[PDB]
Image (cartoon, rainbow, N blue to C red; front, top):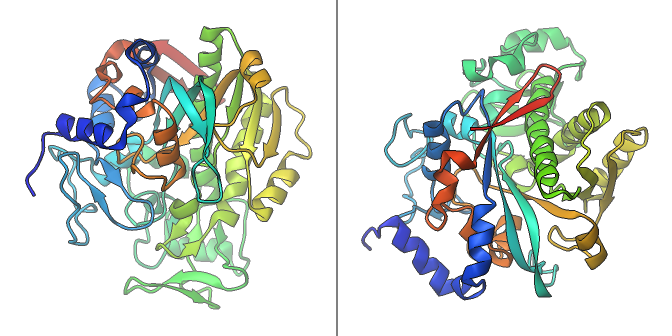
Length: 415
């Protein structure tokens, strides 16, 4: 086929899916006006970087496969390596390093929501009989699926034995960045206050210099996870989110009931698309929330609800928050992200995280294939957070610049 101009491809998809007929034109001018882009100024320092991060992306980036569609309609090549070799300055697509820095934003909108559920097959699609309004916070987490994104920040192996970018120097300051030095500072213990070999149950996850990942019993090639850097990274991401939710509630005069959807896990937490590391990184995610909620007050966040379905994550959550006594109420549930009771909707600002792909249009796939595509079919977010339909997201009056101090307090400046 032939390339379609991107705005027309997008409108075609809306008309072929039925989504254009689901919200009326007075309701969507309101929702589109609520869009905000909270950008960490350390990584997105000016308007041109922010708009680049919002537009220089693919249309669909499939969760399981390496499949997808560009914004002009054409499929991804089946050349391997194509995305790892995108250069800084490419006309249409973000560089790997630009995908790391581009993920340090959050796009929010007070969008309409017509149903809850739909993903996966066991989660039945339940309509709200009158549509409600949820403040939906889209953010991309660390991804370990391939080896040119966050894998290059938090792991040391035989192949890439040294960490790279100065834009992320600070995450590693005071900690090793070379594989052989790390093997020796660990000694023959497996853990340390700052690093840890990865155990897959009992054996090690290790990587041959040829390039392959294999389970091993030998420390010799066992890869090392830079846990203190990953924790510091989560601290920057969570503190940006809490500041933006808090600010959103402040400006609406209600306190938020925040659904803290799990962001980094699932397919993003499988090294080499095979070796699951959820059980290792999930506690550091929760400790970031614990530290920030114990040290800061968020007068406009009433409760945070963690949808947690796995037993290990369940007990991890219970152990990490047994001791938590900070002022924001915190609990876990098995409730769908977009499901609120009607007493919750009167009382609070309903608020939910959209676990987003930084390298695809908000909404991503068009079926019920993921938590994001679910939100994308149950809400107006494709109308509210895609620059094709809502150019206000490129307008600098809708950007909020954010500064994260050394104490992890966040300063928000409008323009």
